[PDB]
Amino acid sequence: RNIAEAYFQNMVETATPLEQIILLYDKAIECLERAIEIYDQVNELEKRKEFVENIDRVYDIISALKSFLDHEKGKEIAKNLDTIYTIILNTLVKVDKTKEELQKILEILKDLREAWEEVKKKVHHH
């Protein structure tokens, strides 16, 4: 049920904040993809450094995404989003994280992002 309630109030038609959410998702997914792409080469001190930087960026954007959440008025929907963000965050901070768990998180970011683009679709047509 309407994931938009996680951040926003019911009868809003102003789309600028919704577009910022999608932007944040966009940026997190692309940095996560990079880090996955170069996970295997982190012996390579250059790739390692780029890996650590991309993971920092995913962690900062999802941290933002989580704390922007409307807990007070966002119902079970904000709470549930918070649960998933929390898991993601706990995964990024793991020192022995695997390429597998990052790949999965990436699918998840992608499904969420799809939920959002389609909220956006719904509000313009209204």
Image (cartoon, helix red, strand yellow):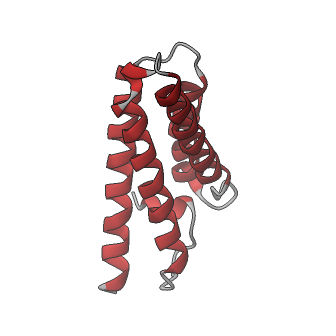
Q: Where is residue 67 in the image (x, y as percent from the top left)?
A: 68, 51
Q: Where is residue 123 in the image (x, y as percent from the top left)?
A: 37, 80
**Residue 70 picture quarter:** bottom right
Left or right, 86 with reference to 120: right
Left or right, 95 with reference to 31: right
**Residue 109 picture quarter:** top left
Q: Which of 21 and 11 is in front in this view?
A: 21
Left or right, 105 with reference to 51: left
- Residue depicted at x 47% and y 16%: 43
- Residue depicted at x 51% and y 33%: 88
Q: Nearer the viewer, residue 75 or 110?
A: 110
Q: Residue furthest top?
A: 96
User: Up-down: is 99 above or below 12?
Assistant: above
Q: Nearer the viewer, residue 55 or 68?
A: 55
- Residue depicted at x 52% and y 69%: 20
The quarter of the image holding the N terminus is bottom left
**Residue 32 picture quarter:** top left
Q: Where is residue 59 in the image (x, y as percent from the top left)?
A: 59, 40
Number of residue marks = 0
- Residue depicted at x 50% and y 37%: 84
Q: Where is residue 18 in the image (x, y as percent from the top left)?
A: 49, 71
